[PDB]
Amino acid sequence: GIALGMIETRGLVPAIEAADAMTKAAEVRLVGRQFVGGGYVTVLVRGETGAVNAAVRAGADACERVGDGLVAAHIIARVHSEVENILPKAPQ
Amino acid sequence: GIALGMIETRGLVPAIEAADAMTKAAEVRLVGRQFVGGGYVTVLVRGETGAVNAAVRAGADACERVGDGLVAAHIIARVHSEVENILPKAPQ
Amino acid sequence: GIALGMIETRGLVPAIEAADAMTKAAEVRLVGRQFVGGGYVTVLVRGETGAVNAAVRAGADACERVGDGLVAAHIIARVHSEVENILPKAPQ
Amino acid sequence: GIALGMIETRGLVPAIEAADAMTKAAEVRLVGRQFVGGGYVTVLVRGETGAVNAAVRAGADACERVGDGLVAAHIIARVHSEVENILPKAPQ
Amino acid sequence: GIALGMIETRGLVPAIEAADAMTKAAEVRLVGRQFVGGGYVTVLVRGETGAVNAAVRAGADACERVGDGLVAAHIIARVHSEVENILPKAPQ
Amino acid sequence: GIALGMIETRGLVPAIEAADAMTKAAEVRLVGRQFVGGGYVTVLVRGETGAVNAAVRAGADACERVGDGLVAAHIIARVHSEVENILPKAPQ
Amino acid sequence: GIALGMIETRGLVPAIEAADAMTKAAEVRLVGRQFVGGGYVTVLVRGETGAVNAAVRAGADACERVGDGLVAAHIIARVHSEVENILPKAPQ
Amino acid sequence: GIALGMIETRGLVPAIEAADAMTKAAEVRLVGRQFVGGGYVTVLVRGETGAVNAAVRAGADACERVGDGLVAAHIIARVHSEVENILPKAPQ
Amino acid sequence: GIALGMIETRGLVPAIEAADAMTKAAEVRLVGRQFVGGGYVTVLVRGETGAVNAAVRAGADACERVGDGLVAAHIIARVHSEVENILPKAPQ
Amino acid sequence: GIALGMIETRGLVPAIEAADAMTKAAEVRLVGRQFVGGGYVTVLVRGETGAVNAAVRAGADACERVGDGLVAAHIIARVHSEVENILPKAPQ
Amino acid sequence: GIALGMIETRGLVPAIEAADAMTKAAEVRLVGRQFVGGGYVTVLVRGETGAVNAAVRAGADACERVGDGLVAAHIIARVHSEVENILPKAPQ
Amino acid sequence: GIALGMIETRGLVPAIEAADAMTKAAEVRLVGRQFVGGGYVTVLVRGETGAVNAAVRAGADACERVGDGLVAAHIIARVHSEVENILPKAPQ
Amino acid sequence: MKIMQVEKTLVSTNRIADMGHKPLLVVWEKPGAPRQVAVDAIGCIPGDWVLCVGSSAAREAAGSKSYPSDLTIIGIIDQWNG
Amino acid sequence: MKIMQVEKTLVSTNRIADMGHKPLLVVWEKPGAPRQVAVDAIGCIPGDWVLCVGSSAAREAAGSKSYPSDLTIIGIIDQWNG
Amino acid sequence: MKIMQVEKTLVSTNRIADMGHKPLLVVWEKPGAPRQVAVDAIGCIPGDWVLCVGSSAAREAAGSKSYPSDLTIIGIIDQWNG
């Protein structure tokens, strides 16, 4: 699907925990891990809206207390094509 | 083993101390060191669950008073196949 | 669908109200009603995650007042293959 | 007649009273008695909506002061085909 | 005689006392003992209305102090035909 | 024998202690052990009257401190013939 | 031997612990785990008297803080032939 | 795997959540879910010691806030052969 | 039978309720409805003693809360032959 | 047409208003207007249970303020055959 | 009927008053008037339970102040079949 | 198994107790019992880390009050390869 | 307001509680026109030509500012020819 | 109010939070008709002929004076055949 | 509510201040249906079949009891084909 689920955490350990949680929670495909700068790492998952919602909730809860924690958890149910150009398609 | 243990530190010196500690304490393989940004370095080890637990604890106890410190210590016993894609395979 | 929705109520009147509500809210199949023991009745539905979410939320709101209430309303988007063996496949 | 009226009581004496009141009050068919566990007994009647409503009101008033009492009296005017598999078809 | 008298007790010993008492006290036939769950046992007798009243009063008195006691004593003079399908015809 | 002695205890351990005691004390036959529900276990012996009296007393004394205890100990010297149907004839 | 050791616990986790403990501690044979109802689970071991004592003490010590705990631990050295019919021969 | 992990919960919903969590957390096989009565459901997993430790910790963290709750979390690292007879082999 | 149960109400609606109730409750035959004047309506039923007792009590209970209410509830168990001339034979 | 709805009012204006309201609200035949005496006037309607319920509720609300008022408004879904004798067939 | 109602008075005048009152009140048959000796006279009636209760109450109230008095009023709804032998069948 | 658990005791008796406890508790293999001199006996187990930790806990508790006592209880999750040569491989 | 003719009565037993004890009537602009249901606050026989009111107003006319109504008969037109 | 038949359920997982947990149903006046969506406050099965309230009232029936609904099902008509 | 397909974005530079910074989209039920403009409260792309609440309810949905919206998009229907 098209939904974007995104969790930004302060540091990588929190994010790996979130990613794991999201992918184990629902049928979401992790499309990216991005080191933003400052110690912010965003992990991005794509899927159908229900899956993305479940995943983001689970991940957020999971990573909240891991390290410096959660900065943001957000669901964008349908993503605009233009925004797709700035979104990682597979991890790297 | 497939478990993942990660320690995030502020600064590389704490991290090298942690990696060293973890690898010595238990049967774990260091698979990565990553620079997150903002001074966070994450050291990642793989092994059996018990070994990984021992290692992370040892590493945390070591890195805690070395440098700016320990930000996070975390074990994930089974990591999803999607998460594996964002995890460093061997140190570099 | 592969998503599990489960509602637990104290008593069966609350459970029927919840199953009805769940099934009505979304396109979800009731695959079981279980008398746990002690007066806990769990009614379980399966469907797509959005459908399951709609159903569980609706059903929980419906049954909270009826009877002695709702003990738990839970959604599991991805159900582990192992857990499916302990899950009802059809309502009897 | 597809409405459902359900009365739950703590114990069988209250329930027999409710059943009798409900059946006498209106043209409903008693389709079941279920021992839930924990002392909960649910007596379920089917019929048209008006009948079910009347029956349920009558029944509740009757069983309130019998034994440990009424836990729940509920009416569902139309029952989903799915919920029909979790409801008794005959009293036995 | 077609009246119904029912006594419900917490535990089986109070119920056997009730049944003995009821049957001895007046012209009633023990038609059933039902284990409700939760520790409730219901003992049911049939007979003429007055005889059933006498029996139930006696039963209540006998079991009030036995075990954990009486929960309910009730008499129904005419039982609707529908109710008869959920009531034990002969003792087991 | 005609007489009936019943001991109800909370849980099977006190009850087995009681059965053992009763059967050892006097010539009474264990005719039933019943799991009532909600933790009530009832152990029933049938014997001649003095024997039953002796057995119940022994059993009651024995189980009062074993486990959660004795709810009730009761003797019925002749039980009406109707009560005999609800009474077990052999321990299941 | 013929001794019986019985541990009753609130819940099955405590009982399994007790059982394991008992079996490891002494030469005893687990003959039954019974769900009494209301959450009481009884685990029963047979063996020689000394062995049985050792087993039950170990079992109790083990399960006292596990879960909701221990309701009863009891040894009966020779049990009446009659009480045998209510005691399980092999675990099921 | 000879280790056993067990989680006892009040109600079935928390237990299914625990089974799911455990099985997702580590390589444990769900061998059974048991209804103990009184509202207790015990979910049991068999795996290697470390895996079981991880899994139980995961289940406990997850099921705690779902439903009425968690009663016990326990690990038996080497289970005796006698105990196996009581433990459920495969989920059904 | 020949016993007479009589209920007096302030108004006819309570009286019809009583009659319905009485007749549903026991085997009594409505022999009359009389408008006394002043707003008193007497509804009279004939049946055997116990049936009549049951019915009158039922009728009383029912009509007490309907309308202006109940003035009298009475049973004449054996009605003298002279009085029969004043009592209504069949309802009108 | 089985159900009976009856409204009693003090005075005839409130009753004509009530009958009018009932008949307008639902498809119920007006089978009678009765002058009880004392000023109690009862208006009685016969229709299906829902129709009768609607009619009666409407009538009651209408006549609450008309005249000296509503004494009673009652619905009987199933009327015992015996009562049908005392109930007016058509208005006159 | 099977019910026995008995009244004992000191002297025959009180007893005839009692009998008359009993037989008039309810449909009971006078089966004996016995001269016990010492001035005790016992008047015994048989009938349906309710009838007998009514009769005995009327009787006892009636004979209380007539002569020397009432000694006893008693009702035994079903007597053991053996007691029937010592009981009078028709009055002398 | 890589991990090592060593418990040192004063005397062989506390040590046998510890060894037994350890070997029973978790799956570890005794690789040695050493008579150090002075009365210190070291019992050494090798297993996977979770197992070794559990075992050492059991052992220490067990031998604390047996005889002279526990001098030490220690765990090394992975020992340097050189240490392996000074470590016993099959029990003496 | 729209003039509609009362056609028949509507009965729903499982209506919401706030709907109240109020009567409900099926109305149409002309026979064969789309059928709508209005709360009756007037007391209207079938075949009457009536004036029905819209959304905010209907609620008050039926009796509470918060009533669950969007159509409510507020009058019967004395002479309307259809 | 309007008489319409529930056709099917509607799931919008990304709906506004204010909508609550309430179920949403696809309702049409007739088959092959414009389809509207209604908050269901009664519990209505597909194929049901139901009564749907208008806008201010819809919010209140749906559960609050400030609920986001413009159409709520308020009762199921006991007998209607369209 | 009504099910509408988002067609295109609507831009009005000189709109009222009360509109806020809120996006407006042109939505039609059917391609070729009359178009309407709905405040987009969810973030809806073109081609989306969406749920649109109407009067009064819309205003609160778009952000205040006083917002000037008579049409808002409350959700995107997950599965819909016309």
Image (spheres, coloured by chain):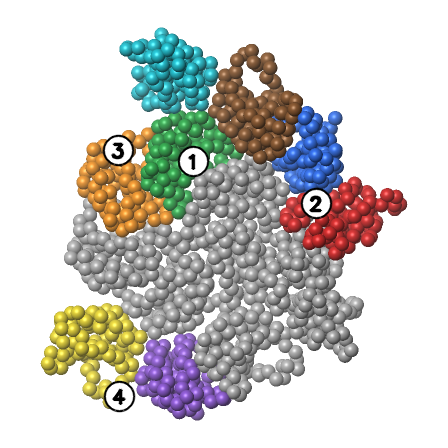
Chain colours: B purple, E green, F orange, I brown, J blue, K cyan, L yellow, M red
Q: What label does residue M22 carry, if any?
A: 2
Give the SS element for disc 3.
strand
State the residue position of label 4.
L81
Residue K10 versus residue B45 in the image, above or below: above
Which secondary structure, mark 4?
helix
Q: In the rendered view, would you say I33 is above or below J45?
A: above
4 and 3 marks in contact (CB < 8 Å): no
Task: Measure the alpha-carbon separation of dots 1 and 4.
Answer: 80 Å
Instruction: For marks 1 and 2, give the CA distance.
Output: 41 Å
Q: Nearer the viewer, residue K59 or J52?
A: K59
* Residue under numbered circle 1: E73
| Residue at image location 22% in from the left, 39% down from the top | F57
The chain to which mark 3 is attached is: F
Circle 1 packing at 10 Å, graded few (<14), some (14-19), many (20+), is many
Tell which of K40 and I26 is nearer to you.
K40
Alpha carbons under labels 3 and 1: distance apart: 26 Å
Residue E61 at least partly seen: yes
Q: CA distance from mark 2 to mark 3?
A: 67 Å
* Label 4 neighbour load within 10 Å: few <14, some 14-19, many 20+: few
Q: Position of residue L68 (x, y in %)?
A: 13, 73
* Front residue of this view, candidates L85 and F62: F62
Q: Are marks 4 and 2 on the same chain?
A: no
Tell me where residue E10 sits by quadrant: top left
Q: CA distance from mark 4 to mark 3?
A: 78 Å
Determine which residue is flagged by label 3.
F3
Farthest left residue?
A: L38
